[PDB]
Length: 200
Length: 200
Length: 200
Ligand SMILES: CC(C)(COP(=O)(O)OP(=O)(O)OC[C@H]1O[C@@H](n2cnc3c(N)ncnc32)[C@H](O)[C@@H]1OP(=O)(O)O)[C@@H](O)C(=O)NCCC(=O)NCCS
Ligand SMILES: CC(C)(COP(=O)(O)OP(=O)(O)OC[C@H]1O[C@@H](n2cnc3c(N)ncnc32)[C@H](O)[C@@H]1OP(=O)(O)O)[C@@H](O)C(=O)NCCC(=O)NCCS
Ligand SMILES: CC(C)(COP(=O)(O)OP(=O)(O)OC[C@H]1O[C@@H](n2cnc3c(N)ncnc32)[C@H](O)[C@@H]1OP(=O)(O)O)[C@@H](O)C(=O)NCCC(=O)NCCS
Image (cartoon, rainbow over all chains, first blue to last red; front, side, top):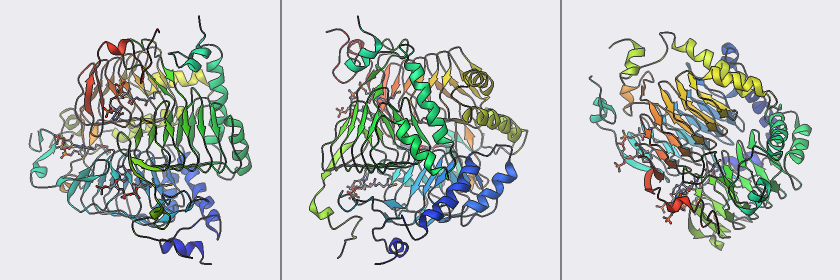
C-alpha cells in the first residue's frame, strides 16, 4: 500500500495501470500523434506542440518528427535542442537534457528497466531511474541510454553506443557497452574530422 | 520441381513475386497502415486490428504503434505480450513468441536473410528460418534477432544485442554478437537493479 | 570563411540556415511526408514520389515506407534498389548507392557529423562527407554508416555494425566498430546460411 507514483520516485518496483497514469499517457500520446502526423509545412503547429508535449523546453528547440515517449511531461529539455528523426524517450520518470544538445537519428533513452528474474516481473513490473544529459552533449545514431545514467557535459557518444554507466564530461565514449574512448584535448580544436584541419 | 511456397518451408532460397505472396503482403500492410496511423484513442479498433494482423494472439496483448512486418500472418503470439514502439518483424516465415514476453522499443526480428554471395542473390534471393522466443523473455532496446534463432524461456537479452546464435533458457545474454553473460540465479529473486532488494 | 554551399563541397564546417537550404529541405520533407503517409494500395503514387524524392533512381527501385532523409535530392540510386522499413539518410551532401543494393530494415546513413569539441559546434556546426555504396552490397539491420565511408562492391555488412571506416569489396564486415570478418570465397557459392548447401 504505497501509491505507484510514490514507488517510482523511490526506485521501487511498480506498475502503471492506475492512479491517473493511463490518463496522463493518453494526453501526452495524443499530442505526440498530432505532432508525428503534422505536415512539414505546419511549422507554428509543430512549434507549439513541442512547448506543449514536454514539461520543459528552452528556446530554439527543434525535433524532427517522429518522436516517441510514454508521457512527455517528464522530459525537461534545455536551450537550443536539436533532435533528429525517431528520438524515443521512455519517460516514466525524470529525463533531463541540458543546453545545446544535439541528438542524431534513432536514439533511445529509457529510465525504465525490468527485473531480470522473470518472477519479479510476472505482471511486467518495472523500476525507473532518471537520466541526465549534460550541456553541449552530442549523441550519435542508434545510441541507447539506460536507466539512471548521467552523461557529463560537453561529452560525445558514438553511434551504436549502449550507455549503461555514467559518462564523465569532456570525453568521447563508444562501444557496447559504452566506454570512455578518450578525453577531448586541444587537438580537437584543430582537427574536426579524421584528417581534416580546421584551417584549410 | 518445387514452388517458392515449398522452398520457404524447406529452408531453400526463394523470391516472393509470385504465388500470391505479394497479394498476401498487401493485405497485411494494409491493416498495418491502419494500425500505425490510428489515433491513440481508437482503443477498441487497435485491439481488433491486432487479432486481425497476426496469425495468433493470446489474451492481453499490447503493441505500441508503429509496428512493421511483412505479412503479419506468419507471427504467432502467446498471452500477456507487450511490445513497445517500433517493433519490426520480418516474417517471410513463421515467428513464434511465448507468454509474458516483453519487448523494449526499436527491436527488429528477422527470419529472413540473403546469401552472402552476391552471385546467389542476383535477383535478391533469400532464405527463411523461423524464430522461436520462449516464455517470460525480456528483450532490450535496439536488439536484432537473426534467422532461425531460438531464445530459451526466462532469458534476458540486453539492449543492442545482435543475436545470431540460439540463447539457452534462464540466462542473461548481451553483446555484439550476443554472448551468454551469466545464469539467472536466486540472487536475482531479491535484487533487480544494482543493489536494490525487495521486502515483504 | 566562404559561402555555405561551398564549405559543404569542400568538407568544411558549416551551418545550414541560409542560401535556400531550409526551403530545399521543406520540399524534401514534403514529398517525404506524402510518401510516408501514402496508403499501401496507392502503388502508382508511391512510384512517382520515389522518382521525385531522390536525385537519381535507376529502374526497379523499391522503398518500403517510412523513409527518412534531410533533403532527398542529394541521393543517387542505381538500379534494383531495395530498402525495407525505416531507412534514414542524412543527405546533407551526396550519397551514392550502386546497383542491386539490398537494405534491411532500420538502417541509418549519415554523411554528416559534428566537431567533437563543443567550442567547434556552439551553433551546431557540422561537416559532410559523401558516402559511396558499391553494387550488390547488402546491409543488415540496425547498421549505421558514418560520414565519408565507401562500401566496396559485393560486400556485406552484418546486422548492427557501426561502419566508421571504408570496407573493401568482396568482404563480410560486422561489429562495433565494423571490421572485416573474412573475404567472400567460393564456399559461399554453395553454402548460403549457417550449414545449408544449394544441391544435396
Ligand atoms: C565518435 C566519432 C565522432 C569518432 O571519434 P574520433 O576521436 O574523432 O574518431 P577516431 O576514429 O579517432 O576514434 C578512434 C578509434 O575508435 C573507434 N570508434 C570511433 N567511433 C566509434 C563508435 N561509434 N563505436 C565504436 N568504436 C568507434 C575507431 O574505429 C578507432 O579505432 P582504432 O582505435 O582501432 O583505430 C565517430 O565514430 C562517430 O560515431 N560519429 C557519429 C556520427 C553520427 O552519428 N552523426 C549523425 C549526424 S547528426
Ligand atoms: C541487460 C541489463 C539488464 C544488464 O544485465 P545485469 O546483469 O543486471 O547488469 P550488469 O551491469 O551486472 O552486467 C555485467 C557486465 O555486462 C555489461 N553489459 C550489460 N548490459 C550490456 C549490454 N546490453 N550490452 C553489452 N554489455 C552489457 C555491463 O556493462 C557489465 O560490464 P563489466 O562486466 O565490465 O563490469 C542492462 O544492460 C540492459 O540492457 N537493460 C535494458 C534496459 C532497457 O532496454 N529498458 C527499456 C524497457 S521498456
Ligand atoms: C553477416 C552474416 C550474413 C553472417 O556472415 P557469415 O559468414 O555467413 O556468418 P558467420 O557466422 O560465419 O560469421 C562468423 C563470425 O562472425 C560473427 N558475426 C556474424 N554476423 C555478425 C554481425 N552482424 N555482427 C557481429 N559479429 C557477427 C559470428 O557470430 C561468428 O562468430 P565466431 O567467429 O566467434 O564463430 C549475418 O551475420 C548477418 O548479419 N545477416 C544479416 C541478417 C539481416 O539483417 N537480414 C535481414 C534481410 S531482409
